[PDB]
Image: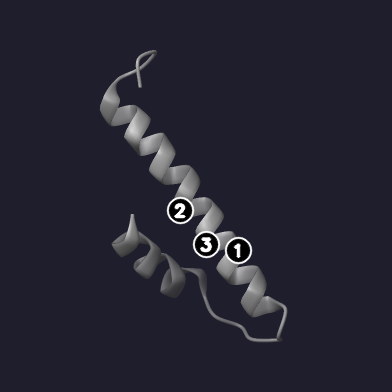
Amino acid sequence: VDKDGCYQAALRGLQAAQKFLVNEVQTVYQSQGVDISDKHIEVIVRQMT
């Protein structure tokens, strides 16, 4: 937040949270043999973040 701008810091934090959430939802769905494309999950993760 202080080494860079507040906007860039918010962008990096939300990007890390988005990557974590997308990867975990995708690996739980892949644990059961269910194939869902990444765009379907990250539309909803975009609405969350």
Screen quadrant of the C terminus? bottom left
The spot of residue 9 in percent (x, y) is 36, 29
Q: Which mark is residue 24?
A: 1
Please provide percent x and percent y for residue 23: 59, 61
Residue 48, percent from left and from top: 33, 61
Q: CA distance from mark 2 to mark 3?
A: 6 Å
Residue bearing the label numbered 2: 18
- The residue at 27%/30% (across/down) is 7
The residue beneath circle 3 is 22
Q: Are marks 3 and 1 in contact (CB under 8 Å)?
A: yes
Secondary structure of the residue carrying numbered label 3? helix
CA–CA distance in space, label 3 to label 1: 6 Å
Q: Residue at x 33, y 35 (%)?
A: 10
Q: Earlier in the sequence, mark 2 or mark 1?
A: 2
Q: Hey, what amino acid is under mark 2?
A: Gln
Residue 43: % across, % down: 36, 68
Up the image or down, 17 lies above or below 39; here it is above
- Callout 3, which amino acid? Val
Q: Nearer the viewer, residue 48 or 15?
A: 48
Q: Identify which residue is drawn at 66% across, 69% down.
A: 27
Q: Mark 2 and 3 residues: CB-CB less than 8 Å, in contact?
A: yes
**Mark 2 and mark 1: Cα distance apart in space:** 10 Å
Q: Is residue 26 left or right of residue 48?
A: right
- Identify the amino acid type marked 1: Glu
Circle 2 Cα neighbour tier, 10 Å, few/some/many (<14 / 14–19 / ≥20): some
Q: Look at the numbered disc 1 and give the secondary structure of its residue.
A: helix
Task: Answer with left or right where residue 29 lies relative to residue 47.
Answer: right
Rendered image: mark on residue 32: none
